[PDB]
Image (cartoon, coloured by chain):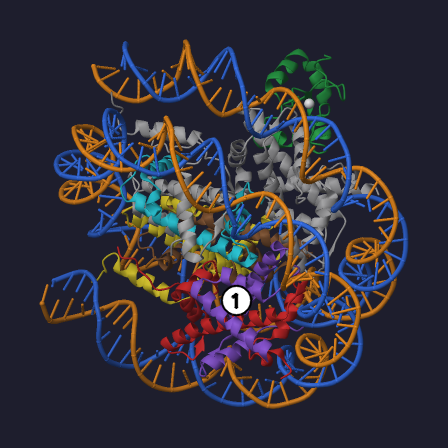
Chain colours: B red, C cyan, D brown, F yellow, G green, H purple, J orange, K blue
Amino acid sequence: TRSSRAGLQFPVGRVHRLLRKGNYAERVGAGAPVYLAAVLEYLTAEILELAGNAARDNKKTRIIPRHLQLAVRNDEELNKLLGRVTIAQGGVLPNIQSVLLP
Amino acid sequence: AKTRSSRAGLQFPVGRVHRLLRKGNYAERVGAGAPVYLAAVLEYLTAEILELAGNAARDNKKTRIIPRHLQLAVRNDEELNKLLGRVTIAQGGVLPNIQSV
Amino acid sequence: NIQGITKPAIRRLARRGGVKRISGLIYEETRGVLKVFLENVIRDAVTYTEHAKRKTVTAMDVVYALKRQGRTLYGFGG
Amino acid sequence: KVLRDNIQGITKPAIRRLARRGGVKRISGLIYEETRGVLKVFLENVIRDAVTYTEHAKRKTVTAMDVVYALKRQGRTLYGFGG
Amino acid sequence: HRYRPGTVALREIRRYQKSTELLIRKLPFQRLVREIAQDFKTDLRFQSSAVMALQEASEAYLVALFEDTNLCAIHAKRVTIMPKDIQLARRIRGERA
Amino acid sequence: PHRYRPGTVALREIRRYQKSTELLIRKLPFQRLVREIAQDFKTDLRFQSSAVMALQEASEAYLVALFEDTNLCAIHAKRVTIMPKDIQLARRIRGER
Amino acid sequence: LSECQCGICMEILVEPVTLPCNHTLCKPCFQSTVEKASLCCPFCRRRVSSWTRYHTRRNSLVNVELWTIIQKHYPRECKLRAS
Amino acid sequence: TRKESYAIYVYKVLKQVHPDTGISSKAMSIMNSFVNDVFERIAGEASRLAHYNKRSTITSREIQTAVRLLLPGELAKHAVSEGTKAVTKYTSA
Amino acid sequence: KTRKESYAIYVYKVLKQVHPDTGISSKAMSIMNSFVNDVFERIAGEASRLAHYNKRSTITSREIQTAVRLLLPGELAKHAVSEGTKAVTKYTSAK
DNA sequence: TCGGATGTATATATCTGACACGTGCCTGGAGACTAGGGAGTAATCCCCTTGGCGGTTAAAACGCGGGGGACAGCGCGTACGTGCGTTTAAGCGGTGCTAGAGCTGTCTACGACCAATTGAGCGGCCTCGGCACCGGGATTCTCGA
DNA sequence: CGAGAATCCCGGTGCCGAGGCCGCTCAATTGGTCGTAGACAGCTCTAGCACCGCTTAAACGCACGTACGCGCTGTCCCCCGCGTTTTAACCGCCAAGGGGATTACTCCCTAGTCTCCAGGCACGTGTCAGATATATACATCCGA
Ligand SMILES: [Zn+2]
C-alpha cells in the first residue's frame, strides 16, 4: 500500500478520499495525503505518549478522559493549541491561590 | 426585462452573485433563487447601515459620510454592534464616554 | 424550574472553581447567566433540527451549535 | 543599516495620549515597559503571519493584503485596505 | 469539636478538584431544558445523549466563570465573591455588552 | 499667576483626543520598529507604506481597548491609578498569553 | 570498557544519553542516529521524540551520574575519543 | 487591470435613501469590504449546512437558515421577510 | 446498520508502538477520533483558503507546509515539518 | 462670593483637490438547448423515546449560634500632574536609482475519469482480567492545650 | 504538645468492559489516456530605498507642591458548621407507539455548451465642500 510505501500508520487512501469529498479544491496533488498523514500521526503519537505517561504516574494501565485532560492542560503549547476545547469528564487541575491557603 | 436584477426589482446583480457562488467551491451545484435571496439580504443590510450613516452625517452638519460617521453609526446601533463586535474600522475613533468616578 | 438548580449544587460548582467564601446573591446571578447560556445554545440547536426536518434534538446538532458558538466539545462522535 | 533599541521610539507622551483616548485619568510610572512589551508580542505574532504569507507567495515585498489577511487569521479583521 | 471556618471549605475544595463526576442532578436539569425548549417550538423530543452534552457544556462554562470571579475578588483584596465581580468578569470577556 | 488643579486638564485632554481621529504614535519611529522586528525573522524584506499604516491602525485599536479594560479593573479596585497588576489582570481575563 | 562502550559504534561512551527504555548511546552518535534521523530507540524502537524535546528544552540529555563515573574510570579513553 | 467593486451599487442605494448625500473613497472602500465580509460568512455557513445535511446543492432554504443563524433576531426577521418577498417576486414574474 | 468509519485501529497501532503495555477505553477512543477529525478539518480548510487566495486551483505539499507553519506553534511545527519532509522524500524515492 | 485668563466655540474667507459626470470600449451577462443525476415521494419496518409506579435512601431544607470578615474613618508620606525652559529629531519636499512586481508565450508533466481487481476494515461474536467496591489499619494532618 | 478523626494505604472478591478472532463487501489499488493548470523564460515600468536640507513642532529635564495610595483601627452582622426533619431524585421494571432509517421510483432542475450584446470598466475634465489660518465672543475655574 501507499502507507507501507512511506512507513506511515495512517490511511493515505482515506485522507485522499476526504480531501476530494470535502470540495476543498478542484484538484489534489499526490504528496498531500502523505504529508497530512505524517503530521496527524506525529500529533497523535505526542498526545498518546503524554497521556500514557500521566496514566502510569497515576498507577493505572489504561488511558481515561482524566488522563487525557492532565496530559493536554499540563503541557504549554498543547494547552495553547487546544485552548478552546472542553473534554468530557476531564475535570480541572489542582490549583489553589496562595492567599486563599490558611 | 432581460437582466435578473430588473426581473426581481433589485439593485445588486444576481448574475454577479451567481458567478461568485459558482467560483467559490461552496457546493457542487447551486440553485436558482439562492442568488436572488442573497442579493435581497445584502441590499437590506446596506440600506440599514446607510440609514444611520446618513443620520449621523446630518447631525454633524456634513454632506458626505466619512469613517467617523460610520463608526458612530455602528457603535450606536445595538444589534449591528453585536454583529460587528470584532471589527476595526480605519480612522473610526472611539465614542465620547467618561466613566462616573 | 429555574430554582431547581439548588444552592448546595451552586456551592459545589464554586468549590470546584476554587472559591472559598460565597455570598447570598451569587445564586440568583448564576441562575441568570446559566439561563442566558442555555437559551442561546438551545436556540441554535433547535434551528438546526428545524432545518433537518426532524422532531428529535440529537447530540450531533448540539455539538455543531457549540462549534458555532466557539465552545467545541469532544466525546460525541464529533 | 542595523537597527537597535527602536522600541524606545514609542515615547511616553505618546503612551499618555493612547491612555487619554482610552479614558484613563491618572497614570503610573511603571506601565510604559508593560505597554512596550505587549505591543512587542502583538507585533511579533502579526509580523510572523504576514511574513509567512509573503514567503508562500514567493515574493520579496510584504503587502497590505498580507497584513490584513494575517489579522483576519488572528480573528481581528480590519476594513478599509482592500478585501 | 468544631473546625474553624474555611478548613472544611478547603477540604471540600481538594475533594471536589480530585473528582471528575458531574455535580448537577439530572432530573431538574432535564426539566429546565424541556421548559426552555417549550417556549421556542412545541412538542420537541430530546436525546438523553443531547441532555448529557448540554450538562457537560454548562458545567464547564460555569466552572470557568467562577474561576474568573475568584480572580477578580482576590484582586479586590476581598475573599468573598460578589455579583459585581461576575458582572465585571463577563464584561471583560465581552459576553455582556 | 494661574495653575489649574490636577484633573481638569486631564478631562480636557481626554475630550480633545476622543473628539479627533488622527494617529498618535509617530510614523517614522513606528516604521523603524516594525522593520527591525521583520529583520529578526527573515532578511531582506521590503514593506508597503499601506502595510505599515495598517499595522499602526491595528496596534492603536488594540492598545486603546487594553487601556479601557485596565481602567475598568483599576476602578473596580477602588483606585484611580492604573498599574502593571491591572494590566496583567486585563490580559489574563481576556485569556491572552 | 565493554559496558562503557555504546554497542553501535563501539567507541567509548562520550556524553552518554540514557533513553527512558534504560538504553544508552554516545552523543555525536545519539544525534546522528536518533535526534535528526528516526527519533526512536535503535534497539527497542521506542518513540522518544517528546523526551528529546523536553530534554533539549532543559539541557539534560547527558546523564551526569554515569558521565562522571565514566570520566573517572576511563579519562584517557574519553580524551582520545574527544581528540 | 479590472478591479471589481460594488461602488455604483452602493451609490444607487445611497441615492435612493438620502438624495442629498455623497460618499467618500475611504467610506466606499469600507462598505465594499463589509459586503464581502458578510458574503463569505453567509456562503460558508450555507456550505457547511449543505455538506452536513448530505445534500449536493445549496438553495433558498439553505441561505434562509444561514441568515437566521447569523443575524440577530430583528435584523434576521426583516432580512428573511425581504428575501422571501424578493424570491416570490422573481418566481412569479 | 450504518457503516460508520473510524480511526480506532490506527490509533491503537500508534499506541502499541509508543507505549506497549497500556490499554484504552472506548470513551478515550472517541475523543481521539474527534481530535483527529478536528485537526484534519482545520488544516484542510486553511489550505483550501490559501489555494483560493493565490489564484491557483491545486492543493499541494507546499500549501500544507505553510498550513502547518501558520497553525501549529513553533517547536511542534518544526518537528511536524521535519517529519513531513522525511515522509514525502521517502515516498517519492519509491514508485 | 466678583474677576482674570485661558481654553473652547464661533464666525468668515479662500484656495484646493476630491468627487461627480460625460464618454467610449470589451468582457461578462443573457438566451437557448440538452441530457443526466439528484431530490421528491410512497411505503415499510423496528428502534428509541415517552409514560407510569413504587422502594430505600441520601440529599435538600430549616434553625441556631458565633466568630471572622467587610466597610468606614483617620493619618502620613510620596509620587505624579503642571508649568517652563531647553534640546532633539520628525515632517515636507525635491532627486536619483534600480530591484522586483506585473504581464505574456510556449510547452509539458501531472492529475481527473474510467474500467478491472482484490484485500484492509467494519459489524459481530466471544472471553477473561483490571479495576470498581469494600472492610481493616496508618497516617497526616486540625484544633484545643 | 496532646488527642482525634479524615484521609491514605491494603488485601479480597467479582463482574462488565476490554482484547482477540471471523468473515465478507465496499473502498483501495492498478493500469491507462487526454487535456490544461502550471513551470519557465523574457521585457518593462511603479515604487521602495536612499539622500539632503530647512523648518518647527514635539520631547526632555527640572522644579514644586498637593491629592491619593497605604497601613492601621474599630465595629457590626453574615456566612459556616452542626444537628434534625422532610422530600424527591435514582433504580428497576413494565407498556406503547411516533418517528428515524432504508429502499424503491420518477420527474424535473441544473452543469455544460454555444451564440449575441450591452451594462460596467477606465480615462478625461470640471467645480464646489471643506481644511487651514485667522479674527472674534463666551464658560468657566481657580486665586483672592
Ligand atoms: Zn530502547
Screen quadrant of the C terminus of chain C: top right
Residue J2 lies, with reference to residue G60, above or below; the image says below
Say whether residue F49 is visible. Answer: no
Pick the front one: D42 or B42: B42
Q: Where is residue D25? Give x, y as percent.
A: 31, 55
Quarter holding residue D58 = bottom right
**Residue at image x 67%, y 14%?**
G75
Quarter holding residue C24 = top left
Q: Quadrant of ligand 1?
A: top right
Q: Which residue is mark 1?
A: H34
Helix, strand or loop at mark 1 = helix
Crowdedness of circle 1 by 10 Å Cα count: few (<14), some, many (20+)?
some
Residue G46 located left or right of residue K135: right
**Residue at image x 52%, y 70%?**
B41
Residue F34 located left or right of residue J30: left
Q: Where is residue G8? Give x, y as percent.
A: 76, 22
**Residue at image x 39%, y 52%?**
C36
Pick the front one: F69 or K37: K37
Residue J5 located left or right of residue K123: left
Q: Amino acid at mark 1?
A: Phe
Residue K118 lies, with reference to residue F69, above or below; the image says below
